Amino acid sequence: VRMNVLADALKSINNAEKRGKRQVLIRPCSKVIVRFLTVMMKHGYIGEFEIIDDHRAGKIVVNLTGRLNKCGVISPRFDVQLKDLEKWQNNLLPSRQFGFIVLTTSAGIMDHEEARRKHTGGKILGFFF
Amino acid sequence: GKCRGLRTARKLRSHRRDQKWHDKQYKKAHLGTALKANPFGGASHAKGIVLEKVGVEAKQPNSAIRKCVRVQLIKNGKKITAFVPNDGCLNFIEENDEVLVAGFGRKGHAVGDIPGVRFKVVKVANVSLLALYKGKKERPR
Amino acid sequence: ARGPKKHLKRVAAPKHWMLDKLTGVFAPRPSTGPHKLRECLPLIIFLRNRLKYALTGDEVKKICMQRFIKIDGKVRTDITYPAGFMDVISIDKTGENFRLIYDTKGRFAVHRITPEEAKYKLCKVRKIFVGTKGIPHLVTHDARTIRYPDPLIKVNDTIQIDLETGKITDFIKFDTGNLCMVTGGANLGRIGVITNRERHPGSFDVVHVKDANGNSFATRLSNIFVIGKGNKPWISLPRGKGIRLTIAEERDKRLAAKQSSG
Amino acid sequence: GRMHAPGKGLSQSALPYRRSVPTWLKLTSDDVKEQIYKLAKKGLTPSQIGVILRDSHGVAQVRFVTGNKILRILKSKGLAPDLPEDLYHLIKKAVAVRKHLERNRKDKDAKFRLILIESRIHRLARYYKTKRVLPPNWKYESSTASALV
Amino acid sequence: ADIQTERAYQKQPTIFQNKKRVLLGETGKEKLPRYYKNIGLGFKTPKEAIEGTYIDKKCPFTGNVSIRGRILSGVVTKMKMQRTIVIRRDYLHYIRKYNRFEKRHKNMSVHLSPCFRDVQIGDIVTVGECRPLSKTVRFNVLKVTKAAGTK
RNA sequence: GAAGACGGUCGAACUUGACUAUCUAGAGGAAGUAAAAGUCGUAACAAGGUUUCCGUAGGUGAACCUGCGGAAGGAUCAUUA
RNA sequence: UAAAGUUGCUGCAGUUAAAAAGCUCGUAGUUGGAUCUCUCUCGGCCGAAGCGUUUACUUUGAAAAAAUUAGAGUGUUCAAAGCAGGCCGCCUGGAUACCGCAGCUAGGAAUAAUGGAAUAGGACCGCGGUUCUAUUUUGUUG
RNA sequence: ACGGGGAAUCAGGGUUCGAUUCCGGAGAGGGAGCCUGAGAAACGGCUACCACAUCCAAGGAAGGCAGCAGGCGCGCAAAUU
């Protein structure tokens, strides 16, 4: 069956970006998916997106700007402390100059740099660069 | 595929532990049959008594007579064939003398042409074969 | 294994003695006494390693058998006598009095005191109990049993003891706003004002203490020792006033002092 | 896909976006409740009741006119069956397969299908027992099944 | 019921029950005071213990045990012993190499007072650590919380 | 108040029963492996000269042969209203 | 031990190189779709006893033997070391970090699990049926 | 297989080692039982049996280096009475 709707969403975005498409349809939507997409957008990686409201679960049309190399999910959602954040960055990110690891912390869903700024660990949702 | 779940630690560790037994080196070093069948009993060297001088025929591509000696180990009374490395070094050995024998370098494996020989003579009569070879020392009288 | 042990390895000794590692295999095993094994300074360590009146333990024995050293007003000839927090060490021959006090690094500093302040000490009462036909007895951190204490005095309070008579002169209650020192844990040797005690029934109470420089820390209730009423200590403090410095601040102070001294 | 078949069928009802009573439908909520009560008294299950309300009375979705689902309506009135409709139909199918198998004992396909049906029955019974719809002592047997049918 | 179901007379040692009687003070029964105490840590004495007749020297409220140390929890899985129940404590053990967890459990035999009626399999019990009560019992049930499925 | 004695208890204790094993006065039987292209054949590799192989059963100096079912890793991706 | 990503959690392979069980069902195990934004009292600008259902998670705090490791200072003649030393009696050090897991503690409340009215024994707002009132009896037993 | 502190290796993760001077345990040839004492089931204490072994005038007596040195033995393998 379908599990980790965030994994399916990120896989759809990645496959559409590999194909050069300007838009991708993500279904079903979720709060985690929307928060991940917003974190992606604030860094300029995907651009604007629209939530289609069907009366069971949302869909998202994400406009794609070809700035995205890889968006991926980390399953299972390993709990990450501030100490292990550097190791996760070394493992998952292509460089120390760009790329973000997205974590869910008690302060919300945010990239690893904002997690360090807020001095909090959390559970790793995925990465994008 | 493999199980990726936060509660799969026991399954992953058990699978790794069972699959390690399919590694030849791990199974060799963790069963005890290899240790019990090792003539040296896990040692690096062993002292033995030369029972006779033998000439082992090199493997098929090569043609030579490798001079070895049948030695019975003092530690367990086990009979092994030990290669006498250099040339004229079989002349330094006499029957029923004590030889210190090491491995042949391949950890229980035959080395080069010499088939089934995994040991080499290091000392004869408490004098190294290399000291006798170069004239540094002479056989005890 | 069988019966008590009588030795103490040099490396297994309390680290605040600042003993070496090459000066023998054994450390002075402190005798049984008022203070614990790991919270005391044996007389040999004080008279040899700190004061340097002796170069060997034999010289410490020679000094002590001349009855030159008094702990809390009583002459002690045991060179391994456990001397601990708040003890007064008096040497009348050289005419100097010290009080065994903690430094912010958690080590017994060589703290000289006046002859007038050597007449008393402070003791934290460890328990109070009615016994023997209704007499209230009070036990202190130095195992001093005092009968008929003031009914206001409770556990965790501090009492000023006149060393000559061993009787209570005054007392400080354990309360917020009272000056105190930390006698155990990471914050050992720090001096500050109690701000909040948060109780854990069935467990250890935790007391929060604010430095005189604004820094705040926490300890267990057993590690608090009330020093004075309010913020004025009833006893003299070391060169540092219980204010622990950071390594950066300590390095800067050391560099500035060496620049201005030589 | 299907629980016990390799099929991956997609056919199903596609509900409209609106959750409102349709314009053509003049039936009030109490009228729909009364029609449901009459249909249940006639001996029809909620699936059948909804089918004939949709097909002859213009009631597209009873939940959007009454505010309640048909099974909940029947439970509130008190004329709902002891065991749920899907479990009852599964037990009926299993009973029919078992009755066929007694006179046709060489039908290995019937035995396979009976095993599948009984697995479905056990899964549904476990679900209903967790949800406390069935008593915790309720068990499916190969002899008392025809009594429940 | 009748608490004298043993070969020795069952009584609370603290309570002196055969005090000198009075004919006018007799009203059908001699009346019996109940010994009970409040265990600490904010645990309330059940109304059963205060107003019961059972004799249980290992009861935290009417017996001779003290609650000191660990306060633990678990779900009741067996009730086949006399005044003792087997609870299951479940947890996750962290394996660092795989950065993962494994479900582990252990069973604790804990004393259950007669003051706790209507305790069921699957109920959660808060137990308190006491002195060794038997070979394997070191905890006493202090509180019972019903399972959500009870009806 | 010693020796000593009865009764308990703890209880070591120069051999029999479950001695799992090993090492052997010990030949036999079946293998395997390494030598040697010695001998009788040519089973396989080409349609290897009966296409090969699988499961199963029987038969044979030996490779192997044959019966039934299967596979193409076939020597046919195809054979015509 | 590394090389060995030839034990692969990170991080391997399984059409033909070694390899997916003949095929389904099935319990444990593992995994599991969307959804929900801080109140009665006390010594008048405070202080709180808490049960807000908890757990995981995360952050903080406490407590946690030295030696070893990391690491600060210090010309052992350098260094490995050592915990010494430095100035013309005096001055100064003998730091600090880490210390996993479990336990303790205080914040956060995203994620994950769980729970709260449905059969109404449902939430709040004021009284009946069986009893004694922790001495409201203070010029005295009551 | 005494446990741990810890050691070797190690990009990250890990793998292996830890008899060995510090902490905790266990034992004093193997078992067992005790006296004394605050503390021992102590062995540089006693009492037996089991194994080994010393002196004897053959009646008896006396043993316990896994303390420091030093022998023997074992071994590839480890120092001064």
Image (cartoon, coloured by chain):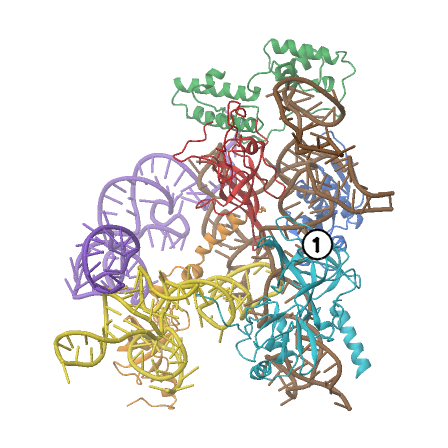
Chain colours: A blue, B orange, C cyan, D green, E red, F purple, G brown, H yellow
Label 1: chain letter = C
User: Can the viewer see residue A3?
Assistant: no
Q: Position of residue G54 (x, y in %)?
A: 64, 41
Q: Position of residue G75 (x, y in %)?
A: 68, 86
Q: Position of residue C233 (x, y in %)?
A: 76, 65
Relative to B95, does residue C158 appear above or below in the rendering?
Answer: above
Looking at the rendered image, the quarter that the C terminus of chain C falls into is bottom right
Q: Judge from the rendering whether residue D20 lies leftward or rightward of residue F69; answer left or right.
A: right
| Nearer the observer, E113 or A20 | E113
| Quarter of image, res C222 | bottom right
| Nearer the observer, E2 or B138 | E2
| Nearer the observer, E139 or G12 | E139
Q: Judge from the rendering whether residue C130 lies leftward or rightward of residue F46; answer left or right.
A: right
Q: Helix or strand or loop: what does disc 1 sit on?
A: loop
Is disc 1 surrounded by few (<14), some (14 to 19) or many (20+) residues within 10 Å? few
Q: Which residue is mark 1?
A: C152
Relative to H28, does residue D82 appear above or below in the rendering?
Answer: above
Looking at the rendered image, the quarter that the N terminus of chain C falls into is bottom left
| Residue shown at the point (62%, 64%) measured from the top left | C144
Name the amino acid type tagged 1.
Answer: Leu
| Residue shown at the point (63%, 18%) measured from the top left | D71
Relative to D86, does residue B80 appear above or below in the rendering?
Answer: below
User: Can the viewer see residue E57?
Assistant: yes
Q: Judge from the rendering whether residue H27 lies leftward or rightward of residue H13; answer left or right.
A: left
Q: Judge from the rendering whether residue D55 lies leftward or rightward of residue B84; answer left or right.
A: right
